[PDB]
Length: 59
Figure 1 (cartoon, rainbow, N blue to C red):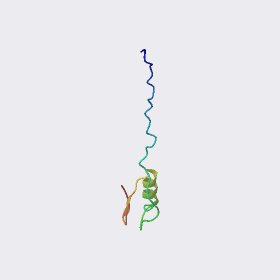
Figure 2 (spheres, one colour):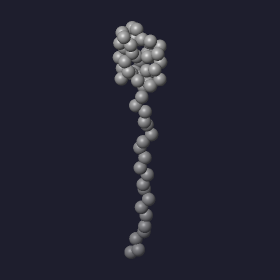
Figure 3 (cartoon, rainbow, N blue to C red):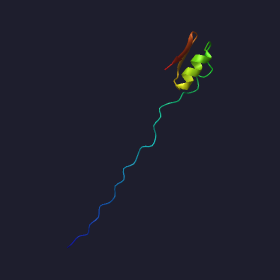
Figure 4 (cartoon, rainbow, N blue to C red):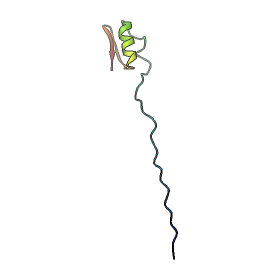
């Protein structure tokens, strides 16, 4: 017989996306009474939450 020899069909590749960061247009200059300090600070961390009359809320 002397059968042949071959078995090279490996690769494994399915991963090239990782972030999970970014708002959805709503916490940007839309609050009633937000301070540039809170807006800038919250924007720097790209954290989105809710706009409070007392200040901005990052979530």
